[PDB]
Length: 260
Image (cartoon, rainbow, N blue to C red; front, side, top):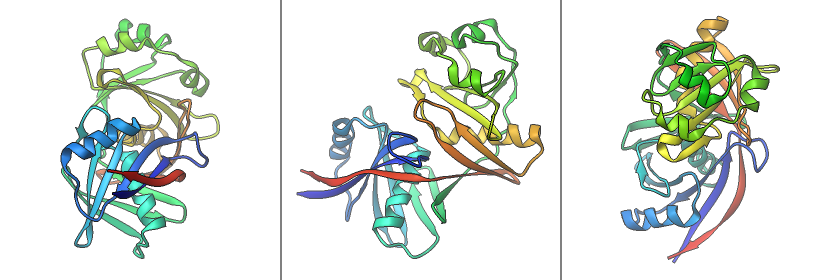
């Protein structure tokens, strides 16, 4: 009847920032329906459910709509609560998702996720792109999402896109916007109107395109980043051969118990 849960703001130093997710560490699996209903109920970005299976932790993510293939901030969140509340001694957690094995590594107050090294390829700068964004796009690229480079951090932060216009664009799943950071290496913001989510405060998977791009362009192995969403979010980045690493802090917003 009682199921402990945690609400954590991933990639946040303090509450109300970063990207929020609810994580449920269960002793056994709940029915698919119940887990879906819980996600609808708390209406948060994503609700992660995990159960220790051997030495790995089986992960499962759900949004208010249905189960997704993967979500980074929610993985970091699940890691955060296992590391801080379920006494895991090892510096690395191993998960067994539907998208294959995942690993998060704790180093001090940071949690590290790994993503594929995917440099986005040049794309034509359509004027309908600059229209939806409401600003000038200096460079354009494509990967899983459209990838536009803007003037500066001030411009990235300030823009307010026509989300209905962006949903209409043909290419990509989402839209990424970047620029040279004022106090950090690079900043970004990610929009996913095609997926109901107008703006993700911090999509880590987007850094598969972000990190490669800025590492090559800035000529560095390590970069500091900040997804300048309203909520904000810091990310420490590293370039490896065929893989990128993002590390971020986390903050517990709430802890409690759900009753079923």
